[PDB]
Image (cartoon, coloured by chain):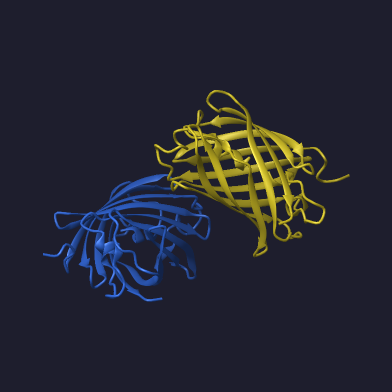
Chain colours: A yellow, B blue
Amino acid sequence: MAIIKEFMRFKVHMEGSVNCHEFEIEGEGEGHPYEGTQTAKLKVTKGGPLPFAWDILSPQFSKAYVKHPADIPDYLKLSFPEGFKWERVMNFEDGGVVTVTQDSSLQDGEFIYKVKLCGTNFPSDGPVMQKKTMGWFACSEQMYPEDGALKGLSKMRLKLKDGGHYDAEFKTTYKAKKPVQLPGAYNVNIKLDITSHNEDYTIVEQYERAEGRHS
Amino acid sequence: MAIIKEFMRFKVHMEGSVNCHEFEIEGEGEGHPYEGTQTAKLKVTKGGPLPFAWDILSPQFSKAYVKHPADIPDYLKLSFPEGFKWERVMNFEDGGVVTVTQDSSLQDGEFIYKVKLCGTNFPSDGPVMQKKTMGWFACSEQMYPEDGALKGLSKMRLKLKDGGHYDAEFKTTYKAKKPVQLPGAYNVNIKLDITSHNEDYTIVEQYERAEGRHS
């Protein structure tokens, strides 16, 4: 039997603060790791309703679910059962910064996600704190190994409610807990959607499709 | 009859938070803008004692006091009386991030400095939150024009109490409030010292010497 089966569920716990508003999120998800597709259902358990845009949190809730061609080593799938950790910084065009620390493991046949998120310097009148965003554009992450780790860089774009867009640079470093084969440089195309939400975004459902491809 | 005289005093007000510990600092300084030298006397007026290292704040307390050769446009000196603004991000080797917003003006023959600082994601056991730093190494700021503004980039190094060092990358964008001539690329060598401090760094005195030179 495989360790990463064709269908895999996950559980996620997020804690952090944005502009020093503390919160906690608990969620459950499921998907098909070799198809590159997944969904999640997130619940704000502390600090709700959030006084900021959900969209800055949605990309933190799953790289084991990336469809990889056979000739591109699936570094983060190979990291299991032990798993991997990743560190991310997001630099937004108006000075806002989000930092993310995450640990992924496999317990009782289910992925376990632990996330720590720290966001700061968002303008009180800006689109994040005023909840003026409407989801991410489809995007591509440029992946490359460096200093024994897998790194990703993406130019991300948030749609704004009244038109136009709001941009951010994503930098992430992924590290397996045990040494496994890193890939060469390649690209991952990502579609991240909010599929449902209640009025104050205390209950949110997400969908993500991610596929790796050669440069 | 000059706007920037050979001897100039300044006043600075800083407010912000680091790992959501809020604080305010008020200070007075003086120096010689054409000699590239200055001193400051800072006091913690709110949120003391600070539960983090003073060294992350000391580089935020004065680019009007940089000695420039005659063939290098002194962009930030020319910006006065109106003055300038700058935005800074500091990325520390252990995931800590500091963002700084600052406004510089000239009122009644004295510089007026207003600083907003936001720091986050510092490990609770790291040298910043454990106050294990002992001042910055001498450093150089690589200056270059870009998108109509003056930018700086520096690789900064903090001494640690028990030996070794703790590194950070500084990126800053300086913008005159009125259009004045930008220089070409050049370097500024900086020595920033804490010359006195009380036991919990609620009163701190600093000294800085800065000189621009061709690359």
- Residue furthest out toward the right: A1
Q: Is residue A33 visible?
A: yes
Report whether A37 appears left or right of B37.
right
Q: Nearer the viewer, residue B26 or B68?
A: B68
**Could you say where residue B40 lies in the image, as x and y percent from the top left?**
25, 62
Report whether B96 appears left or right of A212.
left
Report whether A30 appears left or right of A171.
right
Q: Residue at x 41, y 54 (%)?
A: B52
Q: Quadrant of residue A177?
A: bottom right
**Could you say where residue B176 lies in the image, as x and y percent from the top left?**
30, 56
Q: Residue at x 44, y 48 (%)?
A: A95
Q: Quadrant of residue B2?
A: bottom left
Q: Nearer the viewer, residue B131 or A115?
A: A115
The correct choice, above or below, for A131 with respect to B110 in the image is above
The correct choice, above or below, for B83 with respect to A165 in the image is below
Q: Nearer the viewer, residue B161 or A42?
A: A42
- Residue furthest out toward the top: A199
The correct choice, above or below, for B210 with respect to A194 in the image is below
**Could you say where residue B69 lies in the image, as x and y percent from the top left?**
29, 75
Q: Residue at x 46, y 46 (%)?
A: A96
Quadrant in which the C terminus of chain B appears: bottom left
Q: Quadrant of residue A19?
A: top left
Q: Nearer the viewer, residue B103 or B181?
A: B181
The correct choice, above or below, for A158 with respect to B80 in the image is above
Q: How many marks?
A: 0
Q: Is residue B160 visible?
A: no
**Could you say where residue A43 lies in the image, as x and y percent from the top left?**
60, 30
Quadrant in which the N terminus of chain B appears: bottom left
